[PDB]
Image (tube, rainbow over all chains, first blue to last red; front, side, top):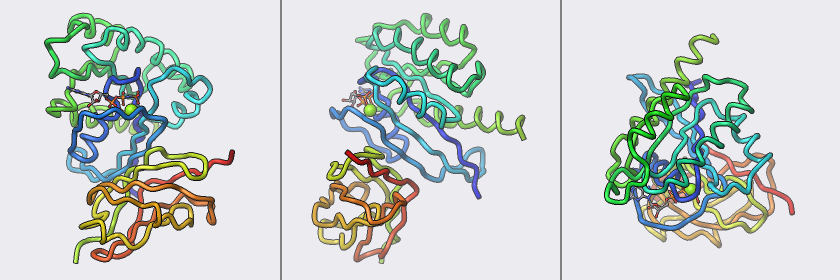
Length: 173
Length: 92
Ligand SMILES: Nc1nc2c(ncn2[C@@H]2O[C@H](COP(=O)(O)OP(=O)(O)NP(=O)(O)O)[C@@H](O)[C@H]2O)c(=O)[nH]1
Ligand SMILES: [Mg+2]
């Protein structure tokens, strides 16, 4: 009977979709290599004082998915589009994910956040803050830099995305 | 003693029989010997269950007996648990 916000993690391989998820879900961070196929998480969280349930579908980075993505994306209400600030390639890949998402959901204003992860590795930054911000404004979505390691802004991106999904459900009901 | 097990994460969330899955949650056991029950889709997976921490257990799924992807963990300390997520058993 509680509200249920369905979030979907998208982005290229190794950008930190799982790390962000596991830090948010279990307050942990471990430097490990474990490519994702498709993982599901769901727990009670308190959003602006109200108890709700967040559901997170953590997906594969590899672009070896085509029609599979469509099904996943269709089941989600909000998306965290993640890339690593240390890998320009993952950043350029976001345009594709965005395209594929807007298509299946048939909504240009679907809850969406551009996430520049691995902010703690400033020394290896390949994507400038300015560049990332401009793209976010072009798509009309917020941009947030995160660190699954120090947890900086991790809770924020999940909460902000939920607030968007929340707002969305207000309008439609 | 402790509270009931609560499975809140499943990785991956689907797979063919005998797929290795990582189970995440709360109160999944105060120790390796605390685990006395592990059923996924009605299938008893206890024999392949490897306790890692109170928030993590790894095991292998087996052929379903149920059509619901329920993940039931039972510990000596907290009893029978529940899950917020489900597993989808795939066919080869
Ligand atoms: N320093 C640092 N390392 C991070 C951060 N986020 C992820 N990492 C590291 O980067 C690696 C890849 O992270 P991971 O979460 O597996 O990436 P992914 O996007 O889920 N991979 P895939 O698409 O293959 O499923 C891991 O070794 C992880 O510890 C971060 O914010 N800071
Ligand atoms: Mg992953």
